[PDB]
Image (spheres, rainbow, N blue to C red):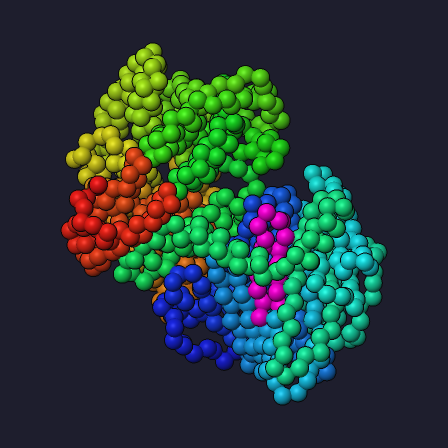
Amino acid sequence: PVPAFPVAEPVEDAGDLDFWNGFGGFAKNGQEYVVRLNGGQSTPHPWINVISNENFGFHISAEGAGFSWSRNSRDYQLTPWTNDPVINRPGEAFYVADVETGKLYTPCAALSRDPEAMFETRHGLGYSILTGVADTLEVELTQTVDREKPVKFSQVIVRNKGSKSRRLKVYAYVEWVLGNNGQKSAPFILSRHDAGSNAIFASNPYSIDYSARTSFLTLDSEASGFTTSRREFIGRFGSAQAPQGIVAGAALSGTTEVDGDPCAALMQEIHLKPGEERHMTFILGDADNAEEAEALVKDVRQADFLSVLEESKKFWTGFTGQLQVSTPDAGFNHMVNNWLPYQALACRILARTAFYQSSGAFGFRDQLQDTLAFPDLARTQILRAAGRQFPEGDVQHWWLPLTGAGVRTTISDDVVWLAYAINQYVSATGDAAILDESIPFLKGPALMPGQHDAFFQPETSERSATLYEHAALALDLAIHRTGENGLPLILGGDWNDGMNRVGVGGKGTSVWLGWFLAGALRDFIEIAEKRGDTDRVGKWASHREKLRHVLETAGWDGSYYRRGYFDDGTPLGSASSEECQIDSLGQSWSVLSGEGEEGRSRQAMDAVMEHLVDEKTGIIRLFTPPFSRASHDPGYIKGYPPGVRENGGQYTHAATWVVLALAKQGRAQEAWNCFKLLNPVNHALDAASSETYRVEPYVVTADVYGEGAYAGRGGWSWYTGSAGWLYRAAVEGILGITRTDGKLHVSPSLPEDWSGFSIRITLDGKARDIAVSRKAGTADVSVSVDG
């Protein structure tokens, strides 16, 4: 029978915690985050930290988790991923239970139900350390991965600070599911073991795309035994806490037959001494082909473990330490300097996977809008994206990282983001040699007018063109796709894909699209003029003038800017409609694009506070009226519950636009208020009050529910499009630091309470300590502003 569930005894609030919450807080310098919890208790949701490589990556929770993938997410995977906040049973487990007494100790909170045990977990930059103290026995687990090698490392250190010699048995548990979905590859998963090399080879020839990928688990020692069937490790009448493979017997038989559940384990008996510690090293790597697999294991086992650890530490310190600030705020320094670049890199470049989201397909709009925070990586990204443009003018919205195949969507905004990125690169770096390069074209079976998208197989063609022509073709197609009213047709959608089927063989359009095209064209005309194309710039200027006239005449609702029109001519974003009363996209981008009138921009900004009054929820909601009934069928957003995600909820990607617009106009106090409001740090969760928040405070979350009795909680964390935008906002709008022509400029608007800040930037190998006084000045020498 089940022996009930043991309740904890709570944990006291100790010192050395800046943001001392009920589970953990900052541990100074903003580099290490410590979580203190007792047995039987855990955070409301798995608090996740991601550590990833160029062709590898995994994320571990504060109480035990694991998700290893080699090539891409949703296509190759090592350990199961369970998006279950309430249970979240880990796919990997480590046991250090004593041989004699049989008492079970684990370094993870979720793997132990003992109320008297001490658990602590740290999630640093590039590594995570889990330590567990249970009855005079201390076990420490370190998580890290290698560079240039798709391999994962795990170090278990057991401290026997007792008075008697103890015999300890160590278990290493792992599950092998090599596919997008479970229970679809388990009957056809094969596992092998080698006597010469202490490793267990796991392969899944059933996978259509991966018929030769091999995975291994090895230890830097000799293995007494091993198991390959969860019917032996866990068996029947047990769970993760009580495997029953540790009580009824202490020997694992070598099995090679396939069962309904694949697993791998390595056995090693340890005879510890009081005051003596042993250092282990568990290897979690994978590589195609048996020869490459054995070469990888023989290199990894022999080379080292720690050297990888300090290599990763120095890598993640140097790349996140390029720009640092010394603002008086205890949350800005601890999060903007390190956590924001760490999250941005490890998510949007290395591993586009979180505990709540999994997306293995590249996005044309995503990566273009992602790298603007920091410069060679931006050039590489924009060159990679330029290769997915068809000669007709459409761009590839999604494509596989390796084969390059993907769907072609009828969306209209994506073809224009290339021009904005080109303009930003030309402004910042100033290298005009990027725009004249040889980029091949891809040929496809095209899209039927009656379907949204088709997958097909793109094939390269022997018709190359320059990047300037690559952007010009897309811009010209956008000009062709303009509607009767003169505004660009939404067609397949806009920046927010939730509002689908607004057009599709109709005259539905969006104002934000027109503003974005005008903003991009205002600089593309100058680029083409400097490259000498009068015919293009003439019509571009004419269309820009007509579009601005339409925006300033037919785009004004009387007190703010409309969103657009429907296929039947019903206005969108207007006050007349019962829903979609105010849309912040157009209001923000009217100021951001630089066109329009200052008075009209200020009037639109006045209506922004109509949805900013929700200070109790602390979110910048996009649409104030919830969408519950489909009066005119705006799209599939109606499926999203009201107050959730884009239906009256929180979208930090569109929320930072308001902060940027406020900062540009000079409303620094309101900009700082919104920045603190948008900051997950100190977002009503200080010690114990915001148990409903349930989400990580040290990283930005895309969606926070703002309506209903369940409002006040975030969602969709660690995978957000607003990390880079938040970093850019913190760099420029609130600090007055920007690099517009390759030379640093200082035009700050300091907060009333801050009253002073100092920054250090290392550009071109020159690290300069820039200190900003109340009005003007610099630490190295007194210099004028914007100099």
Magenta extent: 140-156
The number of numbered badges drawn on the structure is 0
**What kind of secondary structure does the magenta stretch mostly adopt?**
strand
In the depicted structure, whether residue 672 falls above or below residue 237? above
Q: In the figure, is residue 46 to the left or right of 229?
A: left
User: Can the viewer see residue 102?
Assistant: no
Q: Position of residue 327 (x, y in %)?
A: 28, 58
Residue 157 image-quadrant placement? bottom right
For the N terminus, give its image quadrant: bottom right
Q: Nearer the viewer, residue 424 or 325?
A: 325
Residue 661 image-quadrant placement? top left
Q: Position of residue 463 (x, y in %)?
A: 54, 16
Q: Nearer the viewer, residue 763 or 31?
A: 763
In the depicted structure, whether residue 547 falls above or below residue 776? above
Kindly identify the residue that appears in the image at 71 percent across and 75 percent down: 270
Q: Find out whether residue 152 is within the magenta segment.
A: yes
For the C terminus, give its image quadrant: top left
Q: In the figure, is residue 190 to the left or right of 783?
A: right
Q: Nearer the viewer, residue 163 or 131?
A: 163
Q: Find out whether residue 314 is within the magenta segment.
A: no
Query: Given the current orientation, which residue lies at the most extreme bottom position?
Result: 163
Residue 373 image-quadrant placement? top left
User: Can the viewer see residue 121?
Assistant: yes
In the depicted structure, whether residue 90 falls above or below residue 285? below
Kindly identify the residue that appears in the image at 83 percent across and 57 percent down: 256
Q: Position of residue 320 (x, y in %)?
A: 42, 52
Q: Position of residue 174 (x, y in %)?
A: 68, 60
Kindly identify the residue that appears in the image at 34 percent across and 35 percent down: 428
Q: In the figure, is residue 607 to the left or right of 299?
A: left
Kindly identify the residue that appears in the image at 33 percent across and 57 percent down: 332
